[PDB]
Image 1: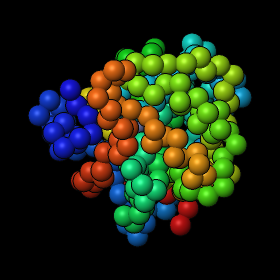
Image 2: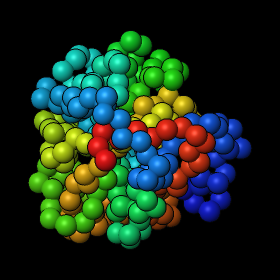
Image 3: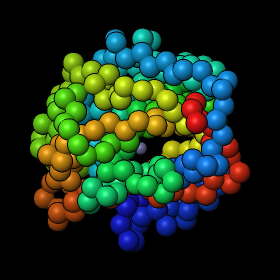
Length: 257
Ligand SMILES: [Zn+2]
């Protein structure tokens, strides 16, 4: 099955998912000299006040916090978007050391981790239908750097010991994803793809310029997770990031210079 290792990782994915070599693959390196400041780009609107988290799960590739997307309120809109998108889940990618782990890079710089908040377009009925459309998803990508602790992340870090292996999950109600956002919503944006198989080219990417700071203690907890199931040989969940893919003449636009 696909994964992140030497024999099933990103260099192999094209054999089962030929779109891996397509025209709008993600992530990408954000070259700040070639990105284009667009003064017409509006502020992002992130409205998480009524977000209803349900559960946290280790799916064997990352851990996901799932949300009740049956109603509005928990919505991403504005910015480069022409529709409204409902939050369905978030997850992270991270490294085997603080010096790598992000999927997007900025002038080739890698962050320790990257948070993906995944939202689907309300034109399309549900997530599964939305991913079949070029504008089906809007993913808010947020870099993590190591520094002070992020208080809003602590509940997440604290629960990870209970979901160590693939197929484990825990109750995870009453979590407020507003605690994962940086102060500034300045962003880069470009059209791209899921960064995991099936790699569908259905995403408007919105990557925040400002990282959030998390502590070394917090990020170390990510690295205790396992790719394997319970009872199987230990395979530590680290380096679950796809490297940057060719931009292929897409334009990355910025809400700032
Ligand atoms: Zn992701």
